[PDB]
Amino acid sequence: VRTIKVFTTVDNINLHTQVVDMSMTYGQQFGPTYLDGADVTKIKPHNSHEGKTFYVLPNDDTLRVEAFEYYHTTDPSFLGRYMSALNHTKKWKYPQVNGLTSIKWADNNCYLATALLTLQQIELKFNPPALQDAYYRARAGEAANFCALILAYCNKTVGELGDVRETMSYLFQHANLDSCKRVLNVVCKTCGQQQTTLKGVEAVMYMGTLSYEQFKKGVQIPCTCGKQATKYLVQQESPFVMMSAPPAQYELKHGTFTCASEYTGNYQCGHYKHITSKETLYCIDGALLTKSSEYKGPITDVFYKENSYTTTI
Ligand SMILES: *[C@H](CC(=O)OCC)C(=O)NNC(=O)CCc1ccccc1C(=O)N[C@H](C)c1cccc(-c2ccsc2)c1
Ligand SMILES: [Cl-]
Ligand SMILES: [Zn+2]
Image (cartoon, rainbow, N blue to C red; front, side):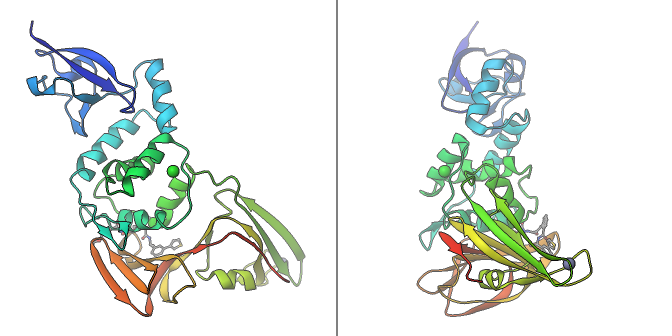
């Protein structure tokens, strides 16, 4: 019987040589099989498949350990969702706008492009080797495998609308933000004063205000005794801070922030645009670049740089 030899893997770095029967589909010999994202499960082997690398699912205990060491996940449907997203993201265009790698618009990838542009402006270190390698190639322009991993880690599908803030929280869980720490103090005239301390992902993000300076001076917050308490940032140890709020009209000044996310649309249905501060105020809409001196628009997320801050109160 005429046969061929292909390579099966779960991480593309540990290849396993397998012989294939050209009269049996890949689904009968290895189960769900993928070739560069293309589902070749119900396809009989071709002569052109000689020596190529095929993605398979972790069926034995050896591949389950190989998969976790690379992706840091035990989800059996991860590679299926990752290969499915890779089939679309490999056909996307990743131009270099303002020295950053963005995505030309396709299949409603506005939140993915806005997220990819933000990660290239913050100091973040991923723990899964899959994200580390893909991010290293995403900066050079090869962001197809990286964007597919983002959809897989977020349980999102190509064409599904997503939130930039929710995409960050999903990716920050796979980052090394353990050294980050935040100290907060909420003061109330009635019940009193109490200091809280946050660490990790919670010490980086905040929902309520877009101004980092107003976070230091204090922001009004409700209380159990029915009084508007004031919460101010006491101490912050992190390479960056993420300030989030519902999309409202906000003014961006030069040098006071790193990058911002613009959201125009209703809840669960809108358009995302990325705004960065460099030589002036730039606005990136996928492959579209727009320079401006000052900006004013519907802002939902603002990102700042930080080392170590301690308030003086
Ligand atoms: C891209 C779309 C596109 O390509 O457009 C073509 C011109 C895309 O994916 N855009 N995103 C989108 O539509 C948002 C969907 C979404 C999904 C899950 C959770 C939230 C959202 C969302 O709507 N987020 C925005 C920022 C938002 C608006 C109003 C209120 C809130 C809010 C959050 C907490 S309290 C209030 C958020
Ligand atoms: Cl990394
Ligand atoms: Zn109180």
